[PDB]
Amino acid sequence: SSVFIFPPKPKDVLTITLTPKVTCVVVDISKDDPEVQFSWFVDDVEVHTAQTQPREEQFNSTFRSVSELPIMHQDWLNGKEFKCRVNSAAFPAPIEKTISKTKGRPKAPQVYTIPPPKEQMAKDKVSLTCMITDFFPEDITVEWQWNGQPAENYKNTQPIMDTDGSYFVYSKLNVQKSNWEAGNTFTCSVLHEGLHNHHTEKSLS
Amino acid sequence: SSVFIFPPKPKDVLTITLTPKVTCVVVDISKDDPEVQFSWFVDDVEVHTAQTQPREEQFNSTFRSVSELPIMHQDWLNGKEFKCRVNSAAFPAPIEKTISKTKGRPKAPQVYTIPPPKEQMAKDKVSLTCMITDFFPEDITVEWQWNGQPAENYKNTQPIMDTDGSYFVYSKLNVQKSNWEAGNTFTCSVLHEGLHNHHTEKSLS
Ligand SMILES: [Cl-]
Ligand SMILES: [Mg+2]
Ligand SMILES: [Mg+2]
Image 1 (tube, rainbow over the protein chains, first blue to last red):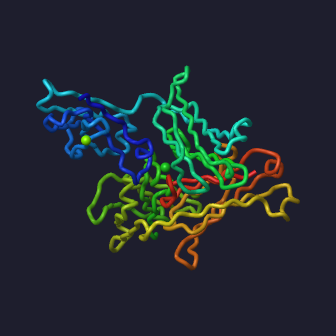
Image 2 (image 1 turned 180 degrees about the vertical axis):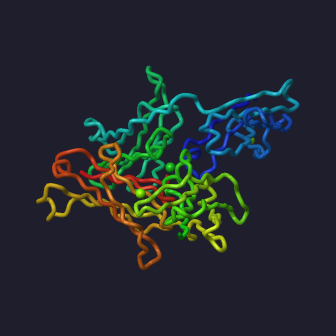
């Protein structure tokens, strides 16, 4: 069992009413292993407000242990370091994991939308595209809105670093024929620390 | 000299990187009056992180004294009460002022845009309109964006309470002829606690 640590949801970090949290996970544990113990520190000073989930059997019959450290929005943006120190019997020494915002001047992303390619219109299931470029750091949230309501039928590619140090991402929203030309409006909502108001919208029809 | 207290900028309250602040002002002071002393409390417990400006001569030759209490975003949204207690020699007893978010379930505003009325197109200076309705509480920020850059040539009416308990606001963006039909894009950016992502955009051309 190897330990992983995850950044907070970019959306959570930017919305005052949400609660950003750092996540530590010990996956691939043997039903036989003793419960792992977690320990957290914010800038090398231990904190005691984390909550660790019970323990859940995953898809490969083994388990995972999740621990969440709720944090302050500002601490993530100001670059504080978050350390998860996990140990147990099945570990000679404890494993330590670290994570913190990528450092550098934030850069605002360029958000563009793309209506179905000329050649796809011939199908009975098309796809709208949101093309987000030149942002930094990589933390970003991209979602789609049908008219004004959520849309769960979309996929975002993981951010990739272009040659120049910035990142890009594509979001693909699928829509069974119809809708597109004759129908409801489609909006690409992006949240990033580099945007004016930290958020922006672009819509298609 | 009567004392006033002002809510934090709605935009400040909602953007994690901005610093919302409560403002106390003692306007109409006589050049002869002794410097007023301020005192703050958050939920009846005094705080000592406020900063009071020196003292500035206003438009009617008299002066004003401004004191700002930086606060936490959450405290404003969670309904905490902010009290400014000001005294001095020119005051028998001290004056106390209170302010805090209006209480009730937040309601999301409906944001619509209006292109110049048919009858105004005949002029060499038109006006775009952003019509925001059904929001609650009244704290809101409405701004305009020419393409993607700020616009300072706009006016927002103060929010008004409709019959049903909600509020509405109109924002008027003026644009010297041209632009409108043949030109750059105009966006109405609104920030409110009741919106998804706390923010939204509507554009015209
Ligand atoms: Cl926001
Ligand atoms: Mg099983
Ligand atoms: Mg003078």
